[PDB]
Image (tube, coloured by chain):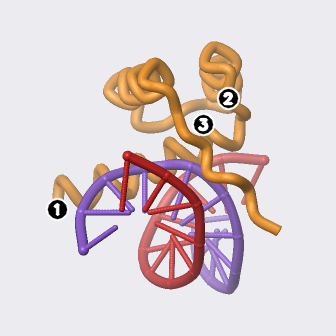
Chain colours: A orange, B purple, C red
Amino acid sequence: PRKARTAFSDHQLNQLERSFERQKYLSVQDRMDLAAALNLTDTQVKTWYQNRRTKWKRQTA
DNA sequence: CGCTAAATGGTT
DNA sequence: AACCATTTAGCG
């Protein structure tokens, strides 16, 4: 039992990256606001942010 | 294969 | 509950 891989829209990727350039971390309230704005789940936004921080560390190494 | 979403197991 | 480090795995 596995979740289908979300395919993010161009609009969703654009707004997640904008969120990340403004704030490396999100409060619970900012995370839930972002998910609602993008029509994603809280956990999909929490996962994108986590994986984005992993990417951020590798490309600043 | 590379990028990156989701899962695993640990940390805090 | 959320994050971290790493692994697993889907898709272009």
Q: Amino acid at mark 1?
A: Ala
Which residue is disc 3 drawn over? A45
Do residues under tags 2 and 1 come within 8 Å of each other at their CB atoms?
no
Residue A35 appears in which quarter of the rendering?
Answer: top right
For residue B1, above or below residue A30 = below
- Provide residue A17's location: percent of width, then percent of height: 37, 29
Label 3 sits on what residue type?
Val
Which corner quadrant holds the N terminus of chain A?
bottom right
Earlier-in-chain disc, 2 versus 3: 2
Question: Which residue, given by chain and number where applicable, does mark 2 sit on?
Answer: A40
Q: Are marks 2 and 3 on the same chain?
A: yes
**Rendered residue at 71%/35% (across/down):** A42
Out of B12 and A54, give the one closest to the viewer: A54
Instruction: Give the CA separation, mark 2 to mark 1.
Output: 30 Å
Q: Secondary structure at mark 2?
A: loop
Q: State left or right for residue A28 relative to residue B3.
A: right
Instruction: Give the percent coordinates (x, y) of residue A47.
Output: 58, 48
Choose top left, top right, bottom left or bottom right for residue A26. Answer: top right
Three-letter residue code for mark 2: Leu
Residues tagged 2 and 3 counted as in contact (Cβ below 8 A): yes
The spot of residue A31 in percent (x, y) is 63, 28
The chain that hosts pointer 2 is: A
| Residue at screen point 70% across, 18% down | A36
Query: Dot 1 corresponds to which residue?
Result: A61
Q: Give the residue drawn at x 69%, y 53%.
A: A4
